[PDB]
Image (tube, rainbow over the protein chains, first blue to last red):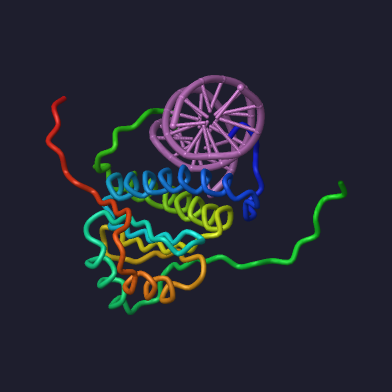
Length: 90
Length: 87
DNA sequence: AACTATTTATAAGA
DNA sequence: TCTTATAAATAGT
């Protein structure tokens, strides 16, 4: 990036859409590279704010999702949590 | 990277494992940033070569997967396909 | 595991 | 979309 940007929701609609398209390609690209380099199985489902779907899966999506739903051990899972935060002085 | 690397399976076991751990964090990180920045719902399931699971989901994994299985329109889908290559 | 040069991604300005 | 300068990730150590 020509500038550092904060990680909060982009407010400009068209900016949000461009950022979405490029970052999504980059993310599927990094997913592909992870799967190849480290010999692992990835499935990546993305729904844009308008509920349109975009997906990546190394092997085969329904294979990976089946394996998921049957997996019955504790495992590393991360998520998004919203925090209350005070801003800078300005 | 201190070196450019080819995109093929890392042969050294321990190298593969370190690369896995760091790149996975980076990938979940970029996923989180995408979901926040562009207000979208992501689900990312990874099974390492030993069949151990690692996951990221912005909202809630079963929510996203339900939405997936019901989605009935054509959509952008990618996968990995193997190519023959000269050196 | 941390730290650093080299690469890979990406945001602003066009 | 493109260009470019800048920030962010990562491959070796």
